[PDB]
Amino acid sequence: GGPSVFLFPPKPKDTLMISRTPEVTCVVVDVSHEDPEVKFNWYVDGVEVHNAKTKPREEQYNSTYRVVSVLTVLHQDWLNGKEYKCKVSNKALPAPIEKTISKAKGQPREPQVYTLPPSRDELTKNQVSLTCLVKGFYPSDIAVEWESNGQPENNYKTTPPVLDSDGSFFLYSKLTVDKSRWQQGNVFSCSVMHEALHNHYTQKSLSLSPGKAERAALEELVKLQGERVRGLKQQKIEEEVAKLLKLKAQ
Amino acid sequence: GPSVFLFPPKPKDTLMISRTPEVTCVVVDVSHEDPEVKFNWYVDGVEVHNAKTKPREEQYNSTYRVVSVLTVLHQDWLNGKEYKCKVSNKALPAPIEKTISKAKGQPREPQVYTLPPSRDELTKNQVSLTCLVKGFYPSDIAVEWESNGQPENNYKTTPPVLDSDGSFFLYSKLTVDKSRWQQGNVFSCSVMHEALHNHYTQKSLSLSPGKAERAALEELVKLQGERVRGLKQQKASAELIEEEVAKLLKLKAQL
Image (cartoon, rainbow over all chains, first blue to last red):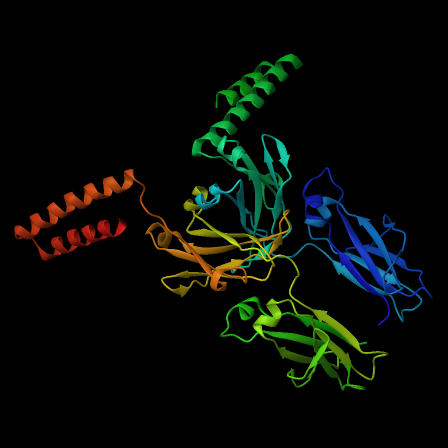
């Protein structure tokens, strides 16, 4: 047993938002101080590529080196299921080691997002738990955050994806808030990114009483469409502005 | 060379006195060149001799996997005693020593909360009953669902997640046909943890009618009772009586 090669996929969030840079990471561990040089060759569907960045080596606790190579990938390439291969050469190896990685294969399935208010039993406590169930998704690569009035909530934790009996995945995200914020009728939003959602995005809202969050969302859309009409009017025209006035009325 | 893993007892086995908690020491990648392996077990530095070694299982890569299982006392494990597995093998420069114990820290009682299905989910054929278990320490816990004193078989539980206050939470999701939920069946989320009285608690969850819905139900019961008594006092088909009596019984059941 000489050096070992491990290959890690991009962060789920990075593959789904076009604004972010998804990268595959090739980690070589148990590199001897004797022969600590490592050459990486990268291949995309068998075709060699040259855009990989090499990180500086790091000392492991067992007085060996860990060496990392990071390859930027195209959103579409990763999601289309292109195979990424890392070939590692080192003098302490009889031959180069190859590892391969790609997105999980299988019929992608759209996540169903369900918000759950606090248990009546939990309303005795000073903090309450807002629950978001995300279920029936494939593959397991997913991102969940919480918002309140278009601003990120930071006091939440998400479970890892769990394999369901039907071969899809589910998880739960738990947002903790002061009971006062809940009782005041604030609207909280569970926001989910996944490859199988329209625009890779959905959100579900949740508040102390039923139609209040639905009414709130409708008013927000009215505001934005009003700004859109005002915008197009200040910009210039008449046909397109009329169509946007029909949207506002809807 | 060979690698040693040490695994703790199943949480349910440490909590029920009827069950046998065991620590498992697994050695993998043992060469059939030097395939003899001696296990020494220590409880808080003190060697013990009650360990049962399983046979030897030639792996696909023509190496051996050897497993040693040490039965532990419920009390010893929960009191946080350290269990050490020392593995000696001629292909090793020195013996490999691995240690395991229950997490150290103030044990904290889990709070159990059942959550009915999202209104949005009641459009679908199956619904999710949710059990939130939070504020527990340490992470060792067991969660099952029951209905009418029988394990429900379509549920999964998440791994314990570390909360921002240093305690753990998880969720257990029971999937049921929406019919079973709608018809007012009681489901129970059952939790075992060292910090619970009797290492056990249960929380139930069902559909029942509100205050206003109960009133309407009582009115229908009255009228259908009059209708049934009417048809019985009169002579109408046992058919029609059967149908009407069945409806009346179903109404009463909903209360």
